[PDB]
Image (spheres, rainbow, N blue to C red):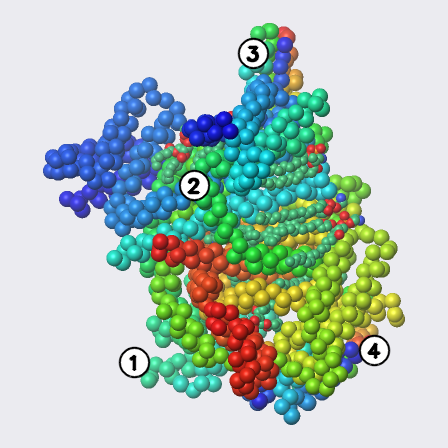
């Protein structure tokens, strides 16, 4: 415990000022494709070793002083010294794994280091805790949005599964036939869907679907993704219009116009209600402090 | 008898009788569609066209 | 003298507001002359009341620690132009600090003076949380640089400006995903940067789910701990004929004469259906005449409205304007309805108070419009092909390559085009900034401002990336901050108007009523009953629903010949199990104590529908795709378990039901605007590639109502506004004179749409606050002290002992049950 | 025939609910009516569908018969259920499943 | 030495303009397909 002498010093503004230095060695890094680099990118892969040997002789000089084999299992009982040891263990593991293998998925943990900024400023700690203890009243709105997205995913998985795979191509080609600022829409030869109007064009199947094959209802996961995107009210009319072109004009508005009334507006009303209620609760509690 | 004597339940219990008669009417009246191939007009129904 | 300062700080704003692109030279002269003349007076009167107020106490006020800054910067800007001063980088700073004389007004309104005094110590309280927000944004920008940085190398020629290639770009992209605008196409480029719609690639979709959800949660926390805590304290700051059936008929008749306006073909005016409704209108008109002519005898606003309305009605049989001002039909049912004229009269109240905040944001919108004019004036022109930079060059034809294939070209004439939303004058800049505040199409203006080159030249890709600040600062001021104190000025018009636990828990005991339980008879009926109402039975029957939901979810498309075959027999198995549990419960509850509970009724309906669906689907191979929906709604039976979810639902649904006229106002607004737009815009042609097309038009009434719902949601409402602007093709069915078919549409559109959004944005807020205000006791309930929940516990324990209501129980059971009930009540 | 039989089933109880304090019996009755209407709606469409695989077409007399009886049976069952179901409680002490 | 800088990128072009201006060559920018034909036929002025 000979290092207890240090940690009491202003050895915390040295550390949160080299935590800010590792936030700039992340911002000035330029990401380039297919395994290319520059000179500045290769310089900052040397600064990583410096930052990695400053945030380890800062912990191994603290896990030897306060914490120990067990001694309390309380130094770790801070919620934050458990974060920094993860943030500085991943840094050694990923810094050695590449030199021994001589992974880029595992380099995406370097973006977690800005969290030591909060684990090192005390005010951020109280703000973060307050923000989280305002999330437990939302346990019933979450359990409701979840089971409503699930119901709408299962309903659209039943009425719309596999109906948006036809579109018009030019006759005898694999070129999709659109107009100036149109985006490829479904088609329905022999039905109530839209018939293709482009001149030299026919309505064939075997098309992946509207947004390069991302927006459609033909398994549970994709149905749930398009329901979520509609419930955020972004691009809900494009999905409505595509279902119109697939199967016809008169029924499918009931599915969408309701999901915007029930999932967007109604649930938002509840969320705002509960949050403001909790805020005034805490306010009238602390106005008595 | 609040649900059985109040008038707003009887207006409905009667307005459904209209649907009852027009429903037994829709089941036996064959006048609800036409064909004109092109005069040989047919009048359709559910039991016989 | 004081009223002779506002003569010169107004004649100054009008000076800097008259500035536009290509102005007549006398205007440039008049402007700089007025600037010199006004700076002279500013300094001279500053000095005059300097010696009239003395040096020391003149420096006392906050708003003259600033005035000398005006006095100094003004003349030093006069002087820097008299130097080797050069290019619009320094120059912008001169002519925009020249705008800080517009800050005088906010000191001048003297309630706007302390409005900002409150605003600034609302932020100072929350600075820590608004720092955690920026830390959040920065971590997600870096994570995006790791995930998608350098991966948008798609081989086509489509331009994807929202990428993660450097730090300022990643920062702009994360901010755009947070405002929610066009986030889905950022997600699609990120899904296609990885494989595609396949197993590893579709999991980049959780970066955007977490981003949107948690970022907007934190934003709600930020901007709701300022309208709930930091404007509740400004409160302490500031405070310290009469025949019933007859009128029911007349208001049923108003409805018929308004529904006669809905269904009318705009395109063909000579529709035999319009001929059928023309006589109907005159019948309705004679009726509405002869029963108010009779009204103006028992006496000599609402009694004069229908007076002014029936006139144009029975006159008809200008033209267009007088058939558009006949939309006053719904505006007669306000007096005939008590609650309607109660609600309408209750919102005109909350307008003359929230008018002080509507005037400060209007002046704040104007200052930013003049900044933007000084930055982006003349720089929003461009060429059809981005290779030609000036207007003399952008002439002739050029090649466009289909799908970026150099061996498939076609000729197009090149033309010098202006952006639809630009910053050339102040009115245009105010329009552009209005559309930016609704978060619609704002990245398209941002990436066109970043590219802005010079006064009459086309864009230069990624020229001025520092020009994003102007936009990100505007959105944070108006669209996030000043919008969340316009909301606070509505709560204080709601929460103001309308111990505390004591009277509310004395009311419960005073009016409460006991339950029923239907304890059975007939030891065999009691026998089955004890099984069917056992708790573990209600766990076994909630496991089978979570198992039936997975089976519906396992369906997919283009499967093979053994998944459907098992699906449709498992469906029969589940139908039979649920029918068995139904008849089981019927045997217990004796068919009379069964239909007393509404969940048992809702379950009987699901059983009867899911049986019929079986037959409809099995008759296919033995001798209506919406009956298959009675298998999914079997999942709302889970609701009966969730006590908290059910009470939350009820508590908000019941308040939606007790506030029907606030929603009637929205219905009325939609009806009026959809009738107007069907006459103003109804003859535009449905062309694909435009925003007035087969899915979105004004030709029918449902089409117009769905278009207005779309604009309320804010989808591309400014792209529809640009599709009705007089340069439009008239559809063939309509009757236009020959040669002139590009005369459809109006510039009235600009009013229409902008007045819709604003009004439709105001009422929605109004309906939200309202619904949250009559629930405030529940949403603010300290569960420690007491609550109706304990009293429902008491009702339950009372009904167990005494199932048949009957009021009374015997003293032994009475005192015995006393141990159960918790300390708060017992 | 299924629809007509549903309505037969609905009428028996919708009447038998009148005597012997059997108010409750208007809840199943109501629901049955709904289903009748429902099936009639189905009926409409299939005939419509066949009409569009067989020339000019027209729905003339009995189509409005069914498109009125179905609509009215649907709304009538739904409203009769809502009038037999007590009330959305509206107050902290009120309950669905209240005594009288 | 004639250098061509192709595409729309954010990278730095000073070095290759220098390579061109040092070794008696020339510097060209090709941002699009419609720019190709004219920029790949113009080196013959320097050679003349
Ligand atoms: C958890 C608590 C709250 C959650 C519960 C809330 C969930 C709300 C569920 C609403 C379901 C959505 C309605 C179904 C959409 C119909 C789709 C459609 O029209 O086209 C596809 C299909 C059309 O398929 P199709 O078969 O025609 O397609 C090809 C064409 N042929 C037939 C020729 C091959 O629709 C139908 O099958 C017919 C539908 C008829 C009318 C359906 C309306 C019944 C539902 C009314 C809902 C009432 C409002 C909501 C109530 C509560 C919500 C506020
Ligand atoms: C476990 C708990 C963790 C979190 C729980 C959830 C916390 C909250 C989560 C997210 C809050 C998102 C807020 C979005 C905007 C807020 C309100 C708003 O401004 O209106 C927007 C509503 O647009 C929506 O996005 C509605 C989303 C509601 C569904 C919630 C998805 C949850 C999915 C689960 C997966 C649209 O309008 P605007 O133009 O953006 O705003 C101005 C409105 N005006 C123009 C009319 C004036
Ligand atoms: C109203 C709008 C407010 C404006 C705020 C703008 C946000 C900061 C902008 C940062 C910036 O412009 O440059 C970032 C630079 C590193 O990247 P750079 O090399 O500039 O990349 C340019 C490539 N063309 O240099 C930086 O990275 C500076 C940012 C440091 C990030 C670390 C943050 C640590 C914790 C947060 C506090 C900061
Ligand atoms: C909490 C507040 C906010 C909530 C935050 C939490 C959000 C997390 C929710 C995200 C879940 C999405 C899961 C998506 C993956 C599901 C599987 C899938 O997407 O693929 C479909 C699969 C078949 O697809 P395919 O690959 O085509 O099959 C072979 C191809 N020939 O077919 C399948 O196998 C799909 C099977 C899934 C069916 C499940 C249906 C719903 C189950 C839930 C019922 C009860 C809810 C949970 C109970 C909790 C109560 C407390
Ligand atoms: C407190 C903060 C709150 C934040 C909420 C967090 C929500 C996170 C959502 C978790 C999603 C995890 C689901 C696991 C995916 C498993 C992979 C998979 O099976 O893919 C299914 C689906 C598409 O099927 P795919 O795999 O492409 O099969 C085609 C043949 N290759 O691939 C998909 O499309 C899956 C996408 C699901 C989107 C669900 C969105 C609902 C959000 C609620
Ligand atoms: C916080 C930091 C945690 C997130 C980092 C973990 C992501 C691992 C990245 C995986 C990866 O880079 O590639 C592996 C895999 C294979 O792809 P690859 O070989 O790269 O080639 C492209 C097509 N396969 O790529 C794939 O095919 C799968 C898609 C890769 C991305 C996985 C999903 C990313 C979701 C990240 C969640 C972000 C939210 C966390 C926010 C933190 C805030 C505290
Ligand atoms: C400090 C000054 C004090 C004075 C303040 C007076 C009160 C103002 C309050 C109204 C708010 C206005 C804000 C809206 C933004 C302004 C829009 C605008 O000015 O557009 C002008 C537009 C020019 O567009 P441009 O692209 O140049 O067109 C070229 C071809 N014509 O050309 C046009 O024709 C646009 C027409 C404008 C229509 C505006 C109608 C708005 C009516 C609002 C009613 C609904 C609000 C209800 C209450 C809301 C919440 C309380
Ligand atoms: C008001 C008068 C101040 C004018 C400020 C200004 O000129 O804005 C410029 C800024 C865009 O930056 P830029 O013009 O590129 O700066 C030179 C870098 N080469 O764009 C802006 O920042 C304009 C907005 C700045 C703040 C306006 C109102 C401030 C209110 C909250 C702070
Ligand atoms: C159809 C006929 C019946 C439909 C559902 C019947 C269940 C029902 O109405 O329950 C009432 C429910 C809560 O009412 P309760 O808990 O009695 O409130 C008193 C507490 N102070 O009120 C509720 O809001 C519970 C949830 C109702 C919405 C669920 C949608 C069901 C229909 C689809
Ligand atoms: C929570 C706060 C936010 C808002 C809360 C309350 C606001 C209410 C506004 C909601 C608006 C959504 C209603 C949308 C209904 C539009 C119907 C539709 O879009 O269907 C299209 C379809 C096309 O058919 P058609 O019109 O004949 O022409 C096509 C080619 N023949 O049409 C058809 O073929 C079928 C015919 C449809 C007729 C049904 C009636 C639809 C409109 C009535 C709803 C209310 C109308 C009054 C105003 C609504 C606003 C309250
Ligand atoms: C409640 C009315 O909302 C609006 O129509 C306004 C928008 C849309 O704001 C929605 C934000 N996404 N943008 C502009 C620029 C407005 C204006 O200039 O008022 C004259 C108002 C406004 C904005 C913020 C606060 C109050 C107000 Cl009345
Ligand atoms: Ca949008």
Kindly report which numbered mark, 3 or 4, lies closer to the viewer in this rendering.
Answer: 3
A194 sits left or right of C212 in the view = right
Q: Residue at x 21, y 44 (%)?
A: C7
Q: Which residue is mark 4?
A: B48
Q: Chain of mark 2?
A: A
Which secondary structure, mark 3? helix
Q: Is mark 2 within 8 Å of ligand 3?
A: no
x then y, percent, for residue D9: 74, 83
Of all chains, the one bearing label 3 is E
C633 relative to A170, above or below: below
Q: Choose mark 4 or mark 2, whichever is in front.
A: 2
Chain of the residue on which disc 1 is drawn:
C
Cα gap from disc 1 to disc 2, whole angstroms: 71 Å
Location of residue C408 (image quadrant) = top right
Q: In the rendered view, tell whether residue C417 sits above or below residue C577.
A: above
Question: Are discs 3 and 2 both within one chain?
Answer: no
What residue sits 60% from the left and 58% below the top? A143
Mark 3 and mark 4 residues within 8 Å of each other at the beta carbon: no
The residue that mark 3 highlights is: E18
The residue to which callout 1 is attached is C300
- The spot of residue A43 in percent (x, y) is 57, 19
Q: Is residue C384 above or below residue A262?
A: above
Q: Does mark 3 have its CB less than 8 Å from ligand 3?
A: no
Q: Which residue is mark 2?
A: A123
């Amino acid at each position: 415990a000979c290092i207890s002498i240090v940690e009491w010093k202003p050895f915390e503004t040295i550390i949160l000022l080299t935590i800010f230095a590792n936030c700039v060695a992340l911002a000035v890094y330029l990401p380039m494709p297919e395994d290319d680099n520059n000179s500045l990118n290769l310089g900052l892969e040397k600064l990583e070793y410096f930052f990695l040997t400053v945030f380890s002789i800062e912990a191994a000089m603290k896990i030897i002083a306060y914490g120990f084999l067990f001694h309390q299992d309380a130094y770790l009982r801070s919620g934050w010294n458990v974060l920094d040891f993860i943030i500085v263990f991943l840094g050694v593991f990923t810094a050695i794994l590449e030199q021994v293998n001589v992974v880029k998925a595992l380099r995406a943990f370097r973006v977690l280091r800005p969290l030591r900024l909060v684990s090192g400023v005390p005010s951020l700690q109280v703000v973060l805790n307050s923000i989280f203890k305002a999330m437990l009243p939302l346990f019933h709105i979450a359990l409701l949005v979840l089971f409503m997205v699930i119901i709408y995913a299962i309903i659209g998985l039943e009425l719309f599964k596999g109906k948006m795979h036809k579109t018009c191509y030019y006759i005898g080609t694999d070129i999709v036939a659109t107009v100036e600022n149109e985006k490829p829409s479904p088609c329905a030869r022999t039905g109530s869907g839209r018939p293709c109007t482009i001149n030299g064009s026919e309505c064939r199947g075997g098309w992946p679907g509207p947004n390069h094959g991302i927006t459609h209802f033909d398994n549970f996961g994709f149905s749930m993704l398009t329901v979520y995107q509609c419930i955020t009210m972004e691009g809900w009319t494009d999905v409505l219009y595509w279902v119109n072109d697939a199967i016809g004009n008169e029924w499918p508005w009931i599915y969408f116009v309701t999901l915007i009334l029930l999932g967007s507006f109604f649930i938002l009303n509840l969320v705002l209600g509960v949050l403001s209620g909790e805020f005034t609760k805490e306010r009238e509690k602390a106005k008595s402090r | 008898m609040s649900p059985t004597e109040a008038p707003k339940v009887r207006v409905t219990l009667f307005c459904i009788l209209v649907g009852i008669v027009l429903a037994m009417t829709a089941v036996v009246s064959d006048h609800w569609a036409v064909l004109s191939p092109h005069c040989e007009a047919a009048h359709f129904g559910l039991w016989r066209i | 003298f004081y009223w002779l300062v506002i003569l010169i700080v107004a004649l100054n704003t009008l000076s800097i507001a008259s500035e536009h692109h290509n102005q007549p030279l006398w205007l440039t002269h008049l402007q700089d002359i007025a600037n010199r003349v006004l700076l002279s007076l500013f300094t001279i009167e500053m000095l005059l009341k300097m010696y009239g107020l003395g040096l020391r106490q003149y420096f006392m006020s906050i708003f003259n620690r600033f005035d000398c800054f005006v006095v100094c910067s003004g003349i030093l800007e006069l002087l820097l132009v008299e130097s080797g001063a050069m290019t619009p980088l320094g120059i912008s700073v001169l002519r925009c600090i020249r705008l800080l004389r517009l800050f005088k007004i906010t000191k001048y309104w003297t309630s706007l003076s302390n409005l900002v005094a409150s605003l600034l110590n609302s932020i100072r309280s929350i600075a820590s949380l608004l720092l955690l927000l920026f830390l959040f944004i920065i971590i997600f920008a870096l994570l995006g640089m790791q995930l998608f940085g350098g991966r948008y190398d798609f081989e086509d020629t489509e331009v994807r400006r929202s990428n993660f290639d450097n730090f300022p770009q990643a920062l702009i992209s994360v901010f755009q995903v947070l405002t929610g605008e066009d986030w889905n196409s950022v997600m699609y480029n990120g899904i296609m940067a990885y494989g595609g719609p396949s197993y590893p690639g579709v999991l980049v979709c959780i970066y955007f789910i977490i981003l949107f959800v948690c970022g907007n949660y934190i934003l709600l926390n930020v901007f709701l701990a300022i309208a709930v805590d930091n404007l509740a304290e400004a409160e302490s700051l500031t405070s310290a004929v009469n025949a019933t059936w007859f009128t029911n008929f007349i208001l049923l008749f108003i409805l018929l004469s308004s529904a006669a306006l809905a269904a009318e073909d705009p395109i063909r005016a000579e529709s035999v259906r319009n001929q059928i409704l023309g006589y109907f209108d005159i019948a309705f008109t004679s009726v509405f005449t002869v029963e108010i002519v009779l009204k103006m005898t028992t006496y000599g606003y609402f009694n004069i409205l229908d007076l002014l309305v029936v006139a144009v009605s029975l006159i008809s049989m200008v033209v267009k304007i007088l058939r558009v001002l006949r939309v006053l039909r719904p505006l007669r049912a306000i007096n005939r309805a008590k609650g309607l004229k109660h609600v309408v009269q209750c919102v005109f109240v909350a307008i003359r108070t929230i008018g002080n905040i509507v005037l400060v944001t209007t002046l704040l919108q104007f200052m930013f419009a003049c900044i933007g004019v000084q930055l982006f004036k003349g720089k929003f022109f461009s060429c059809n092909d981005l290779s030609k930079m000036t207007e003399e060059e952008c002439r002739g034809y050029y090649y466009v390559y289909k799908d970026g294939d150099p061996t498939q070209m076609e000729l197009r004439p090149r033309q010098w085009i202006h952006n639809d939303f630009h910053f050339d004058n102040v009115l245009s800049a105010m329009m552009s900034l209005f559309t930016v505040s609704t978060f619609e199409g704002w990245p398209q203006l941002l990436y066109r401002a970043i590219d802005s080159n010079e006064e009459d030249m086309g864009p230069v890709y990624n020229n001025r990336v520092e020009m994003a600040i102007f936009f990100i600062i505007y959105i944070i001021l108006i669209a996030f901050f000043m919008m969340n104190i316009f909301v606070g000025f509505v709560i204080v018009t709601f929460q103001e108007q309308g111990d505390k636990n004591q009277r509310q828990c004395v009311q419960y005991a005073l009016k409460a009523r006991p339950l029923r339980c239907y304890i059975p008879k007939n030891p065999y009926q009691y026998q089955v009953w004890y099984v069917v109402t056992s708790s573990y039975f209600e766990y076994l029957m909630f496991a089978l629903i979570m198992l039936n939901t997975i089976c519906l979810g396992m369906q997919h498309y283009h499967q093979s010949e053994e998944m459907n075959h098992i699906s449709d027999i498992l469906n029969v198995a589940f139908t039979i199990i649920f029918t068995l549990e139904m008849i089981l419960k019927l045997l217990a509850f004796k068919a009379r104590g069964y239909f007393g509970d509404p969940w048992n009724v809702f379950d009987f309906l699901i059983v009867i529908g899911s049986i019929i669906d079986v037959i409809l689907s099995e008759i296919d191979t033995f001798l209506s795709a919406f009956f298959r929906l009675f298998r999914v709604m079997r999942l709302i039976k889970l609701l009966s378990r969730a006590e908290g979810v059910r009470t939350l639902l009820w508590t908000f649904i019941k308040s939606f039901q007790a506030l029907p006229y606030v929603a009637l106002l929205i219905v009325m607004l939609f009806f009026i605007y959809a009738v107007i737009g069907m006459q103003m815009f109804g003859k535009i042609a449905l062309v694909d590639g435009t925003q007035i097309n087969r899915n979105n038009n004004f030709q029918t009434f449902p089409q117009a109502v769905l278009l207005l719902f779309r604009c309320a949601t804010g989808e591309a409402w400014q792209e529809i506004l640009l599709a009705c602007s007089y340069g439009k093709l008239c559809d063939p069915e309509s009757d236009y004179a020959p040669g002139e078919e590009y005369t459809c549409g109006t510039n009235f559109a600009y009013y229409y749409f902008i007045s819709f959004y604003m009004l439709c944005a105001f009422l929605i807020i109004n309906l939200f606050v309202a619904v949250i205000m009559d629930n405030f006791d529940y949403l603010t309930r300290d569960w420690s002290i007491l609550g109706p929940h304990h009293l429902d516990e008491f009702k339950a324990i009372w009904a167990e002992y005494d199932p048949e209501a009957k009021g009374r129980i015997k003293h032994l059971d009475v005192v015995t049950l006393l141990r159960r009930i918790q300390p708060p009540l017992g | 025939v299924f629809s007509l039989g549903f309505l037969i089933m609905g009428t028996i109880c919708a009447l038998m609910a009148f005597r012997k304090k059997r108010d409750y019996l208007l809840r199943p009755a109501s629901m049955f009516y709904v289903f009748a209407g429902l099936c009639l709606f189905v009926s409409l469409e299939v005939m419509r569908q066949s009409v569009k695989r067989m020339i000019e077409y027209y729905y003339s007399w009995s189509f409005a018969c069914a498109c009125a009886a179905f609509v009215l049976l649907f709304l009538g069952g739904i409203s009769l259920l809502l009038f037999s179901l007590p009330r959305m409680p509206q107050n902290p002490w009120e309950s669905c499943m209240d005594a009288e | 030495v004639f250098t061509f800088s192709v595409g729309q990128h954010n990278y730095d072009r000073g070095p290759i303009q220098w390579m061109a201006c040092e070794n008696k060559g020339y510097y060209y920018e090709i941002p699009s397909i419609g720019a190709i034909r004219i920029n790949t036929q113009e080196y013959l002025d320097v050679l003349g």
